Length: 240
Image 1 (spheres, helix red, strand yellow):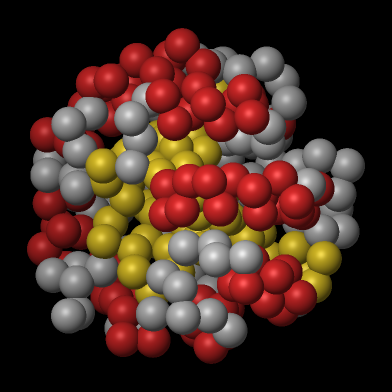
Image 2 (tube, rainbow, N blue to C red):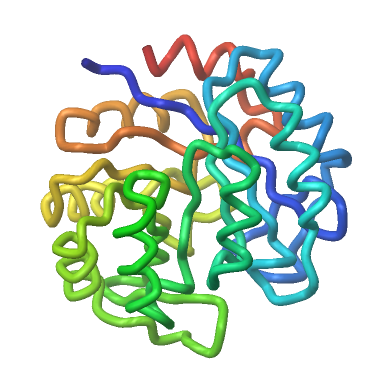
């Protein structure tokens, strides 16, 4: 009923809260302590934290203990992502008591594993779709991931509860969300869609909120909050 969920992000690389541009390794701007960033969002009224281990995502080690420390400090909902691609990584992620995880690369690379984990864990699983036109991209050996609609059909029919949708071209660039893409994904499923990437302004958040009736549930917000484009309090006011 008009409300858009907001998920301020903390992405971790080499023990730091960082923002990348187009999700590309080596474009890091560091914002200091992940724990302090997460604590600040929570103090500012966040209902969700979107917490990401980028080292795990990129295959350059991991920040497992730090990610756990951050999650333990949260009294709010936590959506956890980054290199979750096998049983052991999934087990540790879920042991945080996070509200849900995101699987990204895994859905392209081992579709049978994603099917199994959806079946076993239900709506504790959401799948990230990283879209270039109509093609999906991952972080393993797969620049080609598959056709967007074929992957959505397979995941829909396997019972996937929720999708996290990113246009790599808008990521960390502050150029506005890809509304056409979000709406195209809403056409292709009845499951909730979470927008990820591209937010630069309060008006961008209002535009994403305008898609709630079409099936967009929330928006993950990174660079604009760290850049102080607006305060989390202002964002919360604008998204009902």
